[PDB]
Image (cartoon, rainbow over all chains, first blue to last red; front, side):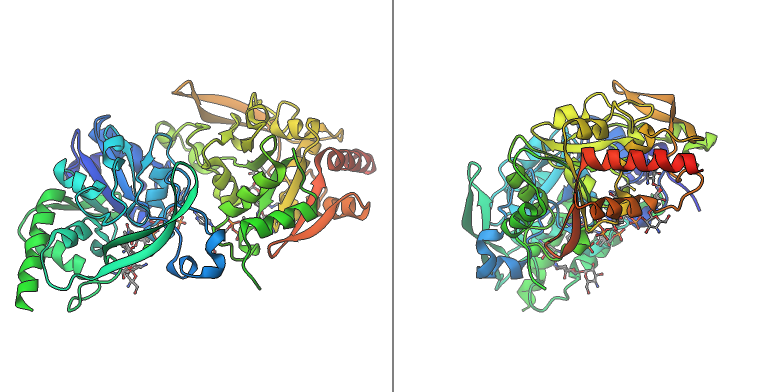
Length: 260
Length: 260
Ligand SMILES: CC(C)(COP(=O)(O)OP(=O)(O)OC[C@H]1O[C@@H](n2cnc3c(N)ncnc32)[C@H](O)[C@@H]1OP(=O)(O)O)[C@@H](O)C(=O)NCCC(=O)NCCS
Ligand SMILES: CC(C)(COP(=O)(O)OP(=O)(O)OC[C@H]1O[C@@H](n2cnc3c(N)ncnc32)[C@H](O)[C@@H]1OP(=O)(O)O)[C@@H](O)C(=O)NCCC(=O)NCCS
Ligand SMILES: CN[C@@H]1[C@@H](O[C@H]2O[C@H](CO)[C@@H](N)[C@H](O)[C@H]2O)O[C@H]2C[C@@H](N)[C@@H](O[C@H]3[C@H](O)[C@@H](O)[C@H](N)C[C@@H]3N)O[C@@H]2[C@@H]1O
Ligand SMILES: CN[C@@H]1[C@@H](O[C@H]2O[C@H](CO)[C@@H](N)[C@H](O)[C@H]2O)O[C@H]2C[C@@H](N)[C@@H](O[C@H]3[C@H](O)[C@@H](O)[C@H](N)C[C@@H]3N)O[C@@H]2[C@@H]1O
Ligand SMILES: [Cl-]
């Protein structure tokens, strides 16, 4: 029965630990926030108020081409190329990355399935030079979030949607990492070309693990007393430092893979 | 029962009457088109291929401020002012105006409740200088649609959502037109100010007619033979000359006003 404002959301964000100059990747379930006077745009505006102009807000866009269409040779010349300026975010990830992507000023990185939207003082740097292959590795917004000592805010989102952990999956040395190869269309100086891609499998976990095991790792991280929980509006939310939870998740995975 | 492509939708638009250099207002129910390979963006892409670069495609954006919150004094300072670059389309008009508005190169006119989104060769003209009061009058994208001799296409949409006919309500001489007055926040060169507004009532029909009466007027115009029906992908869709349906509607309303 409580309605949120740009001002009250800024206090909530400061209360969970958002600070001046932060860079924050956000995963959101916006319905959990509850009634907002100015719609969910008040959340992004509140965040920009807190972190200031030097800060950056990010979201995981991906794109909408499903595998079964991509793999259907009949529709091959009817599939539109991925275009960081025009391709819309995968709807599976909710409105939040679309909200960012279509805010004037936002930029969107180049590696389609891993592509990120960002707005703020380092939006250019965070989206620049996104490797097409292994796009969850060091040459990616996720690696740059670790380098920048950014944060990840789960805004009512289930903890297994923390995509930053796919970057730990990339770094961790464990046996039998599944490698995925696929063909997708992209623009090379404004013209459509089909390109072969390669990356570590993000869609399914390492064999032996439950499909939602990212959530277990996050809770085990919060159990050490690092990170913070809080209400953003009415959404139960989590804020964690990106570098710490990736080091935690790397050795969680490296230790598990040794037992096999 | 089949998939539509940017090229399949292209030939469907040419058969309804879309032609080179056209400027067309679109009201859409996109779930009625069926499955499209590259999503509803393939619709707007097709149209811009049919009409060519001099063409122009429009949508009725409006905005999301709710009367209730607007008229709550306690919420006054928390209302985001209307911003033609940022305030999102009213969701009751469907995704289509948002689809246009969030396309790079697209423009949005200044008068909030009557705001229109536009992309194409004449997008700057169709959106320039939209009057804040009586925003369905002559100083309006709908007035310019008549002057440009454009078209309207109901793309699976209920024919009573044809907003151009509100422009016929502004123009037609019939007694007891209901004037609406309200205060609303608007961005004036980046700064929010509350401004009083007035216009003819678009939210309820003139006292004496059914709510969906716009619809019966449309198909009656179709009985004259001066419209064209046809299926866009899977959607039953109507295309109509703008200048003629206004005159047909104006005379309809003025003639009916005397009987009353
Ligand atoms: C799946 C998931 C998104 C569902 O969350 P949800 O709250 O149900 O859906 P969304 O987050 O899209 O938010 C919905 C709110 O959009 C607002 N919204 C959407 N578009 C809007 C618009 N154009 N204008 C105003 N509001 C809009 C609404 O409040 C809509 O709610 P309503 O339609 O019920 O009114 C959530 O559980 C989740 O998993 N989030 C994280 C996803 C992620 O980042 N995944 C990474 C890869 S694993
Ligand atoms: C109310 C009305 C809009 C409902 O239409 P609808 O087809 O059910 O809904 P929309 O037209 O918004 O289109 C829905 C399709 O959006 C696609 N779409 C929406 N957003 C998308 C996105 N971001 N990315 C990819 N696809 C998206 C989907 O196919 C969505 O369907 P799904 O959610 O079932 O998959 C329609 O009946 C109507 O009355 N239209 C006319 C509105 C108008 O012009 N009013 C004028 C003022 S009175
Ligand atoms: C860990 N579980 C996740 C699942 O959870 C969601 O669906 C479940 C269905 O039972 C629900 N129980 C659960 O509540 C809900 O959150 O959603 C699927 C969606 C699917 N397109 C893919 O996305 C991945 C992309 O394929 C990949 O490209 C991207 N990099 C990462 C995406 N997560 O894999 C995830 C993953 O399997
Ligand atoms: C006449 N019907 C319309 C309704 O759609 C539905 O109407 C009937 C129910 O009422 C249904 N039977 C019908 O299937 C369906 O089309 O949507 C509402 C949405 C509301 N924001 C307002 O928009 C108006 C704006 O408020 C106003 O600012 C603008 N100028 C004109 C808009 N129509 O009034 C319309 C109008 O009442
Ligand atoms: Cl995918």
